[PDB]
Amino acid sequence: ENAARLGRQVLGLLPPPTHRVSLTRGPEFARGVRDLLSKYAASTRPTVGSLHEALRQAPFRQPTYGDFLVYSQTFSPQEPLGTFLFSFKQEDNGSSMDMLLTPTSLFMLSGMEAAKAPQTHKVAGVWYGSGSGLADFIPNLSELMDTGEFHTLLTPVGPMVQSVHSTFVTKVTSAMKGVGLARRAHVGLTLPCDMLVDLDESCREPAGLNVTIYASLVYLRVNQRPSMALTFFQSGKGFAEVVAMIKDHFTDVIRTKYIQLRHELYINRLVFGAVCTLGTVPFDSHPVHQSLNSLPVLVFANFEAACGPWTVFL
Amino acid sequence: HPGFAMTVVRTDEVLAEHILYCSRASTSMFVGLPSVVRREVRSDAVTFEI
Amino acid sequence: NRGLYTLVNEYSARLAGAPATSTTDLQYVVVNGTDVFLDQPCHMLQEAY
Amino acid sequence: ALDKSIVVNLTSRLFADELAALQSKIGSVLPLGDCHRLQNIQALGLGCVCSRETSPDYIQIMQYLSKCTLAVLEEVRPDSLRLTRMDPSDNLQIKNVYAPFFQWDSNTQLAVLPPLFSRKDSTIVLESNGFDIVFPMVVPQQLGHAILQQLLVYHIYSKISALDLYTTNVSFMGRTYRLDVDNTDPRTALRVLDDLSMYLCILSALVPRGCLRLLTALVRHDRHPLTEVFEGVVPDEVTRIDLDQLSVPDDITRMRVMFSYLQSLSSIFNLGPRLHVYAYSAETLAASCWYSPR
Amino acid sequence: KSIVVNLTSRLFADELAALQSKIGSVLPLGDCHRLQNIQALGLGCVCSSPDYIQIMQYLSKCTLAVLEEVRPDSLRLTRMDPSDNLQIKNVYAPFFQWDSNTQLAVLPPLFSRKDSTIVLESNGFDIVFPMVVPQQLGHAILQQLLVYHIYSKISAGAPGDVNMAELDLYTTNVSFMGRTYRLDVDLRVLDDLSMYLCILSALVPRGCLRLLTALVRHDRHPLTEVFEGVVPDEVTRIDLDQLSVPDDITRMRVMFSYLQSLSSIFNLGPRLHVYAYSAETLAASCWYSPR
């Protein structure tokens, strides 16, 4: 009996069969074309059964999940689901490990100032008691920021789907393409309001089909030491505008950077930033403000992930 | 006073409530039948349009 | 300049040459006429009161 | 399958003269505003950004054009315009219509450009409706970049002067064409040039010393087919950098840092979206391209 | 997604096991239908006196495919769609030790032929494999072999300028992912970039003073005030008066054309994103995103 219940569930999720109209016989052509036209006419009327038949045509592509394996002190158990994930792959470890950097954990490596980030500085300290367990695993947090090679090592991955945290080894599953299904709900990418800088706000541009989210990683000096600052942007203005709009955002940084480079010139010092292409939110799906424990976090919906190479801007 | 006067032009709006009269049998109306064709498919929603 | 039976037919249909906006701060010029319910009689009579 | 159609309702029956001008433009790509089915005519063409009373800004029009959704015209009625639209990856049929004719083949690229050669040829007016539909032009990338080459030359030298054979004419293979840059606003075309000036005095700050010497061993010694712009007179600045010696571990960095600022110049030499053509029929002028934005 | 390459003459026993190794490999293919010959697959139309940019621009205009089965009478392919999950074996010569979660690229071949091509004599057409390297290595493998191709032209005419003991110390040793790779060099592939990067090498110092002194006005962009203090002192002494104005136009219509065709060949996208890899099975699942 219980094996027959599964026979009704598999045979109710099958794809619809393709119509086989025989073009060689006389009456068999007439009765096969008639069942195309007795069936399109019952998929056009606004009745409920016609709408009941209309969704079995499912041309869905699928998310491709990546199973990572991180140390538990470089990745908090208190991470919001939908956090963006990077991968730092400087060398070949002796064991099969990986270093995944969330944008609140990359705030502790960078050391960018809390005047820029007032709320994600209190959060990044209460999860990371010293900030040393991150910085001990990167021996070049000064030579990768001087030469400008830190953005060449990060690969963007996608939002987080599952976090099985343990004492020493944390299993992290991401969604590298498509909309990530939880492990069942659809996990949208969650960014803090502290990092995301909109470009579509203004005082009539086209309502396009799509709007993209970029990731800028910007080299700068603080305390006369090399540091950096990672911000997120969101617009659908095409690639030529946004690179010209990000240069307007960092006008105050470049003018305070080359006061020191007017003294001395190294060719390791000229490269400044890099813009990635993370993914595409659909148009006018507004993000919903949430709070954590009070952390303003924009969670999107239907965020499918992409992957762009880091292109330099200056 | 400089040696020239000037004329000054404005525009002003008025929220008016209107009266529409329309006589008997002035227009013949033809009404079709509705039909449902879908045109946006996502992971969350499948939108239709009648 | 056309005859006045082709001006009455065109009167209520066409939104005339560049009228002002509705509910703004500095009275901008209108575009795309989405729900714009305007009646300007000084554009035809060519007078001001 | 999924639906993609954009019908445009004409609020007044258009004339018989301007109906033939639209039906000549059948199968022509034109950018519209929003991605939904019933559309107004004032959001149909490119005429929202290319006016008559104001000076058209060909960067700003082209800058506007990679924002929009693009559609392909399919049927012109006297009461309606039906348009199919362009999904970001879908095999769709397209037709070569445009009046400065250029031959296409398979495995070519295309790019959608503002009406650069003739504004009056692209703009057809609907005086029965009060709007002008401004078609763009689709041009392969070896010519499509070449107009953005010649247009950025014009806004440099005409600001130096304020002559019409070098700064304006576009040299295609065997042909020269005049650009319509008589009454233009340059205020964003100088913004791109103000962005070149940052990259160009960075690429000059890290020139590799070995490549300067390979000119001086070739501009006066032998014949190369494309060095003939340089005559036997070397530039005066090449030898005034030649004076120091060569060094490999100081030129690997001067090539790697020079490698990254050439990737950054694809944000300043952009065309619009691309049309990957995979088939073409010259008896019908009806290609079938494969759309990809950005 | 299947493409059959017919072979009207059967294979040799030496040529069979040469392709049994390369059983998963990305191959260009001049058209995307299936009924094609042995002369269609590979870079044999352009590599068999090869030039660089003609092959790099060919890959973006192409439809790549993946071998799946090597049988005696024929071959079998698999057409690789935009954003399509696959399983590609690392078989490429020379070996580069791919990492998981990387961004693989497809480059034209520029090393020796016995690593690049497989010589076939059963039908008389030698097939050419491309260079499938990670993206950060494949651009560091070429910003040195373009430096090495310059100094092998300076020391060919002026042999006292280039030290061979220091030229073959840095240019032929590439370190990536903590691993140093020594590359094999006897370069007629890169004899066009060396003639484009040098024909652009002189016009850039003349071009920036021509373009800084043209954009001087009240509405100057504020950052270009700061980017003026980077260009050296000798570039700020160039006399633009030694040329004429109709000669100065052709040093921009040519100048910018080597800043576009030289830029839009490095931002080409026949790349594929490996998301799972095992270093001893050499298998890699990925997805392919064109441009």
Image (tube, coloured by chain):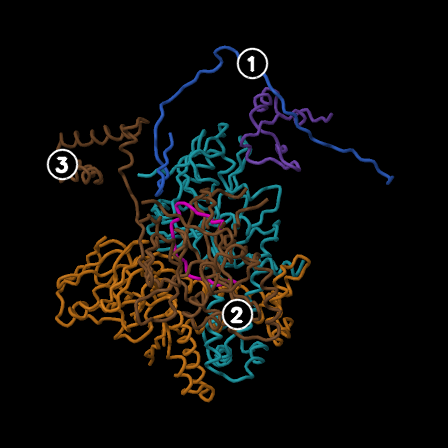
Chain colours: A brown, B blue, C purple, D cyan, E orange
What residue sits 36% from the left and 62% below the top?
A: A72
Q: Is residue E254 visible?
A: no
Report in which chain the residue with disc 2 lies.
A
Front: mark 3 or 1: 1
**What residue is pinned by disc 2?**
A226
Q: Earlier in the sequence, mark 2 or mark 3?
A: 3
The segment highlighted magenta reads A295-313
Report in which chain the residue with disc 3 lies.
A
Quadrant where the N terminus of chain C is found in the figure: top right
**Does residue E60 lie above or below E91 as drawn?**
above
Q: State the CA–CA distance, disc 3 to disc 1.
A: 65 Å
Front: mark 2 or 1: 2
Mark 1 nearby-residue class (10 Å; few <14, some 14–19, many ≥20): few
**What residue is pinned by disc 3?**
A24
The foreground one among D218 and E30 is E30
**What residue is pinned by disc 1?**
B21
Q: Position of residue A155 (x, y in %)?
A: 39, 62
Q: State the CA–CA distance, disc 2 to disc 3.
A: 77 Å
